[PDB]
Image (tube, rainbow over all chains, first blue to last red; front, side, top):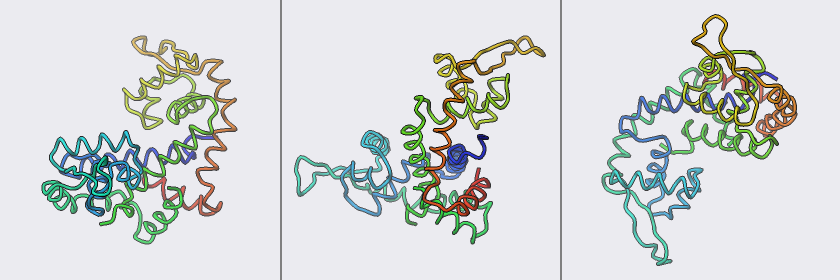
Length: 134
Length: 134
């Protein structure tokens, strides 16, 4: 039992390295999860907050605060669920849409650097193996 | 640009799953990093707190944090660095050494469950591929 063979320690370190490349590379001052929620709201259009959470592996409490921090920046809009007036839908602002487009190149670059230690073949193997551990 | 393809999203989810298996499986109420620090002090013996951090990918404030919580549970002992009396060394308690032993089985089991979706050869491939993304 050595620590450096434990897959949890390894996962954390890969996670920490990614966090470092992302903070260095993204250019818009957003966190990884802030970006994930922004990206996802661009895919979905108007979406319940907790559902947005469940599509980005985020808690109600976690997504709550990501969306609020995204709000403080003017990047989201809220509006009544048309099928349930007790309910809110979260959507990308025009500025939040422009932020997404302005961030694509850098997010692509952060992702390419994360995988850089690996050949394009190896990247595919890793993504497949790691997808099964999600 | 689909989110589910981004290695950052994938890493976070693999990490959250590991966290869930670990909380379910450890049996002694320690976090992954608390456990990592504990395991590492078993390997190193008396060791400076900041060096302990640099051996477990934890910065000064982070390593400070888990050592204090480890101390609250009676699992560590502090003593003066014999080559530098300004300095402290951190070491396992008898109780902390017992905790490590009592925890080995479950940490092994958490680790095997984490990797369970993969064949024993696929694990080796993944461990190798991931090592290089650390």
